[PDB]
Length: 213
Length: 213
Length: 166
Image 1 (cartoon, rainbow over the protein chains, first blue to last red):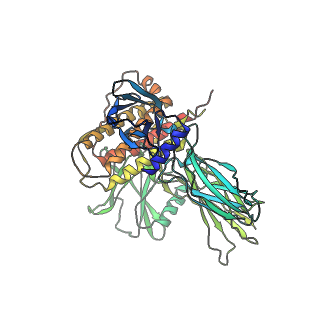
Image 2 (cartoon, each protein chain N blue to C red; image 1 turned 45 degrees about the horizontal axis):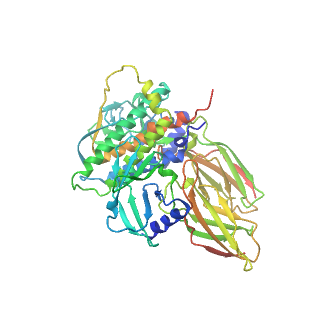
Image 3 (tube, rainbow over the protein chains, first blue to last red; image 1 turned 90 degrees about the vertical axis):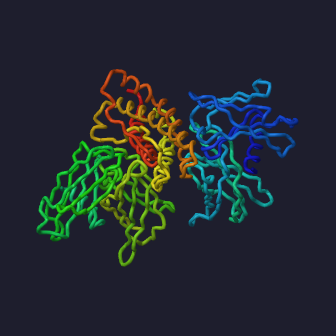
């Protein structure tokens, strides 16, 4: 599961080796943690329990995996019926001995890691000569009206060293009118949910697009 | 049946031969039709039955009046007590001979027909957005937040077919582009309650406004 | 000021569109969608004439309690579905989204003050339910799910959100 693997890598980086959880399409949730590969007693080594506010404590079958680092990641994918946004989700991981390892309380809508935007295209505006950037939001994702973006624009005489433009949520277009003439530029977009209704971490950058001014 | 007649006319003009039902204030409902069959068709020529889901069958008082070109228009003004939305409404029109004329199931909230929007104001833009259009929701009409619009751009005859633009619900202004210069344009705007809560039909066009480019 | 999260149309709309798809998809049900029993559901009809004339607090009562009954109806549908190797492959996800969505809406409504208002406006003895609507197919269950959220729920939420200070 490349996408999940690569995403769990971002969180491992940005966040803690603690219990990390993230939703991609708001109708899902996976929590996981990595740990110094041991011996036997894999997923059995622990019990992952969760409880959505006002409901009974449930268990979530754990899975073990070979993290492309040399360690082992334990992960659980919440049953879809329990992936409710805006409701306190208490998570708890217990080791074989019965001792608590992790204790978190999250809100699914605040841990979203979106797939990267798709279909990035760059065109020279209508008689303005400006660059108009258009793209599609992460596929199969709801609440697109709440997805803001960040554009990376780089290029120049072997001096292409970026610049970042923040795009309003719901907007999938960006107008650049101060770009240097006769210059081959390269742009890319990344997505993330807008606060305060939502929260999360930057998505992967979209495939790039080059344009000559 | 004043502004009513026009509305009735508007729906018939676009949907002849079938049973058309509509509501203007969600507190009302009128189902009707025109007969290209006269003489012998008395007031007891048809029986109009209806049933709100999980409600007992009921009969509606029919009405008749000379119409169009040598035709008659039958109608039933649903008692307010039974004009409830968000629930299936089965309708059945039967000839005095026990013959089935019409049969339908509709949702009152899905057959709304509003008054046309007003105060349209077409203006030019010192930008590539040629003409900026702004308007007002149909007068006396709540829930404005979910009223959808459609603007029409009329050319300077000789040819100039059309240009239909749909305006997202709630939004009462737009930027028109690709407006050829040296031309007199006329723009009008339509309106209709938007899904998923409502639905219905396009209102009559608003009074037009012209502008030269 | 906008009573947070549910007062954001787009937030509430996510669920309304989910319900529409659920309802739409269950119209091609056939004989593969029986609940094999009568599941009590709320009444979703709204008489706009009577609706706008009743004490606003009563809107709260209707929606909060109706939603509660709805949640129970869907939950029952979920367990009824877990049992058997019965047909209709589409049913599962729509039910899981409904259970999930209803759970979010319930939390969302309370923050809006729906549960508080509903309990007080309903703290005096009244007349027997005198109604009792039910469904025996997933089709009616989902149609009711959509009509309720897009109906009185939306209606109640729209009015309640317009609450500054006076």
